[PDB]
Length: 95
Image (cartoon, rainbow, N blue to C red; front, side, top):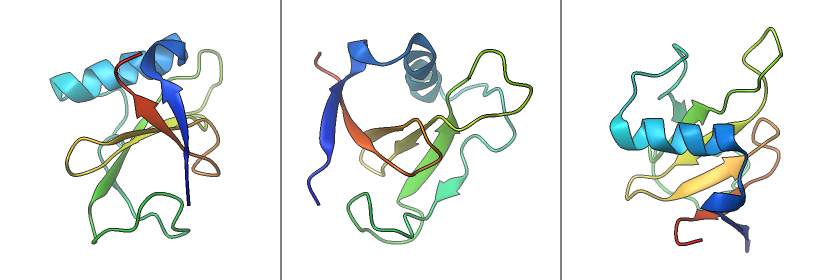
C-alpha cells in the first residue's frame, strides 16, 4: 500500500517539535510517549513486533492529549498521523 509523502518543513510546528524531541530522546511531555505501536491495520509496512513506536504531537488548546502522532520505525523511518492512526504519511526529511 503506497503511502503519501509529506515534507518535514510542511508539517505543523508541533509535529516538527516532536521530531526534534525524538532525535534528542526526550524528555517527553507524556507518559505514553515512546510506547509501541502495533500497526494492527497494516497501514505502515508490516514488520515484526515492536518495530514501531508512537509519540504525541501537541495540540495547543485541548485539555487532553489529542489525536496527532509521529510513529517511528526501527531503522529511523518517520510517519505522520493527525487522526489517531487512521492515516499515515511518510515524512520526507529532505524538504
